[PDB]
Image (cartoon, coloured by chain):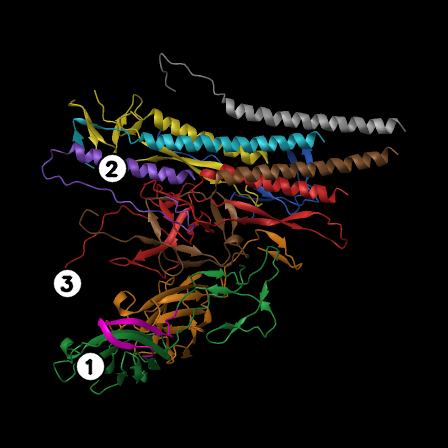
Chain colours: A brown, B cyan, D blue, E red, F yellow, G orange, H green, I purple
Amino acid sequence: YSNEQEQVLGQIVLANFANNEGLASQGDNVWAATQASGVALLGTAGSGNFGKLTNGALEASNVDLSKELVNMIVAQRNYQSNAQTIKTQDQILNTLVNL
Amino acid sequence: GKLTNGALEASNVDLSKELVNMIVAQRNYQSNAQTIKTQDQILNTLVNL
Amino acid sequence: GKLTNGALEASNVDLSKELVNMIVAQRNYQSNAQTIKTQDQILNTLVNL
Amino acid sequence: YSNEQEQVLGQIVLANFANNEGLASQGDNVWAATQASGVALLGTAGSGNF
Amino acid sequence: SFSQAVSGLNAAATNLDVIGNNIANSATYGFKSGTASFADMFAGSKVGLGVKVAGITQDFTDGTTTNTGRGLDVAISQNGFFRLVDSNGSVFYSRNGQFKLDENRNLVNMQGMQLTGYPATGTPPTIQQGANPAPITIPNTLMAAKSTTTA
Amino acid sequence: SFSQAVSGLNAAATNLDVIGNNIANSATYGFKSGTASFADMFAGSKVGLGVKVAGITQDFTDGTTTNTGRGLDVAISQNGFFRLVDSNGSVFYSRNGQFK
Amino acid sequence: SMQINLNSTDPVPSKTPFSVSDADSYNKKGTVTVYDSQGNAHDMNVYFVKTKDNEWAVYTHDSSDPAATAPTTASTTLKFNENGILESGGTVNITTGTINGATAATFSLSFLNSMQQNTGANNIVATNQNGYKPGDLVSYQINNDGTVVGN
Amino acid sequence: LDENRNLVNMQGMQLTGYPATGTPPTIQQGANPAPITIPNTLMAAKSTTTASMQINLNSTDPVPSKTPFSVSDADSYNKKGTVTVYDSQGNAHDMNVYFVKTKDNEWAVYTHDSSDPAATAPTTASTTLKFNENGILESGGTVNITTGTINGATAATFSLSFLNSMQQNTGANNIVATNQNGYKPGDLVSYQINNDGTVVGN
Amino acid sequence: SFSQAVSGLNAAATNLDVIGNNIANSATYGFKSGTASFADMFAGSKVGLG
């Protein structure tokens, strides 16, 4: 304030879950707690089992582009292999029908 | 805030940050283009069965 | 709206967004042609009975 | 409006059915209510089962 | 007999879609990558009926912390989730720390979801670490004065 | 399928347009930088339908003050906006302090 | 139910008697949201005040009732043994107030599994209650074991 | 890690293994495998039952000048050390151990609890460490020590050891090792699986 | 990947700006010089991001 005095308006609460993999993503970089993830355990930053908060900073995504590209290549090759299997079954069925 | 006479507030655009972000963005765009290329090859493979 | 003299309103066609749609529509067209070919083979195997 | 004030004209209604699969398609990306689907339940977006 | 080949093609398509989605959300502060988990579906016979996707598992590893600077921006380290509420009272969780004050002076993210926390009450206000979490507000009302009682 | 990659390309293009607007406006008194904020589009399935541009956020950091020697030039330090009126009486707000 | 952990090193508050407005008059405050017969939310505040080592007076108040009487008598007394395990006073029957004519709810509040040892500070391990508010059907599902569940 | 704190695979089948029983918990391999669970159950405190203080002593130290002993006066003793023990509630008791050289190779050690404000200062020898011809500890290496009663917690009595302590021409008296088996309550911070299959919660 | 080099470049730019500001105030009565303080940004992985 302007009177050389400050006030506290609130304290941001943090949530921790037993099962992180159980949280169902609802989009808009937002998660919703469900049965598999359990009930949310609430607390404050830096106390208990919570990490502290960094001010003036944002956490970026953990997506590495190189690994994604290589996995895309491998998955494309696997998809084409499965398509080859489908073609094999097609030729087998065509051979039997042409009998 | 107070007003300073005889001067202007310049832009807050730092050029080095913009250049680095441009490099990152272009690469991301190229990665997404590669994704589209992969899915295009997938659809071609399935069609040509 | 306002009128700006000495200026022209360019088109609103973005080439990137278009080329991608061209690829997608090409794939849809090829899929429909594949369906046509499938029905053609259906009629063929029925006729040759 | 131009008088620095906004005015509401209406609210879009949303309809949910007990049986979506029972809806009889009429074409033109349009569905029609039938006995199999049941009577449509009306409501507002973002509330209840909407 | 396409029982296996069709399932394999579907699994490969799912994995490729997951990879493409990961590529697309590369610049989404608060995004965690995903990986498809596959399982076979042997059923009675030994012929290996096919494959199925057992689920999609997130990768909840902390991303790089970038000092954008905007004061409201808060990055979270280690474990924890930011808690938000929509207009209908539902509770949601997010690692994205890009916040702004709306017209009613309520801390909201880009989508308008109200950030929650322990509110303060009393004179002087004290953080009610017990009080059920409430949306955080930053009123601009003028602050009253306290008569001198201890010096 | 195609939708995820299309959304990713659109988001990358929007980011690049924001960067281009910022870099072309590096020399503009009172201009504030912009940054695109992205959000994913999960809907029911866990497949991650894609990404979308949640918005473009301005950065209202006080820029460097540059003198010019003109008596009608004034800059707002810290917070504050110049209030302006057009021909129709509509109100507007700007940080640029070049007046004539 | 309210499982809490209390610190054995906390000094006895100076400001006798206990006052809800006086923060210095109590050691710890917690909140539990219960629901009455009609479905109104009662934010029951539970206050822990240390009296003598191995003794904690517990007071209760209704923060949703504007006509609730100010608590002047200790609601119960938690006594922890020399090993820090709760020995007596862990259960007490508590009745809330009346809001807009709704029937007050009488429920048993249990401090089972609460322990007093040398922790960092007073922290509430867990809170739970078996009441709820009216709910509308949102979704339905069939689980792995065949049970049909409506959320 | 599911909602019930068990280790399960993607399909939900629970991983099995040898459970841990006893205090301190150890893997008992004589039992049948059981599903592995990781509870948040706070860990209780352990009052100390065994403490150890290995120290090296200087031979050239002169005897204390200001007889008698006072815990307040620094010149009244040769050395002072601190060991933190824990009672039934996990409260910290700071045992100060005082070394006064009495005769050649003979060192009286006093024990005083500084965490209890109402405890009286020791006036009589708690133990007399005897060092042989060359450091080698001779006798008096183990002493029963009783804590004070603080905040209603049970006082923890324990055996405090000076084994392998030496007294030679070392430059000065400095503590080499202090250990104790007690700990204060702690909450679950992390969990890990070792390369030998053990699941360990930190 | 890119974030590490981005952070390094931003730190170097901040140091350069601080040095330039100090030089610009070479003749400024009562001015005290400034120096940037740097710290690594390890987060979980042993790579040490930035």
Direction from residue A77 to residue H4 in the image, left or right: left
> Residue H177 magenta-drawn?
yes
Q: Quadrant of the C terminus of chain E?
A: bottom left
Instruction: Depth check: give the residue in front, G67 or E3.
Output: E3
Instruction: Depth check: give the residue in front, H193 or G25.
Output: H193
Residue at point 30%, 77% (across, down):
H165
- Image height of H59 relative to A35, above or below: below
Residue at point 28%, 53% (across, down):
A8
Residue underneath mark 3: E150
Marks 1 and 2 close (CB-CB < 8 Å): no
Direction from residue H8 to residue H106 in the image, left or right: left
Please give the chain letter of the residue carrying mark 1.
H
Please give the chain letter of the residue carrying mark 3.
E
Residue at point 44%, 56% (across, down):
A16
**Residues rendered magenta in the picture:** H162-185
Q: Which mark is residue F79?
A: 2
Q: x%, y% of residue H47? A: 37, 77
User: At label 2, which amino acid type do we have?
Assistant: Asn
- Image height of H52 relative to F15, above or below: below
Direction from residue D26 to residue H77 in the image, left or right: left
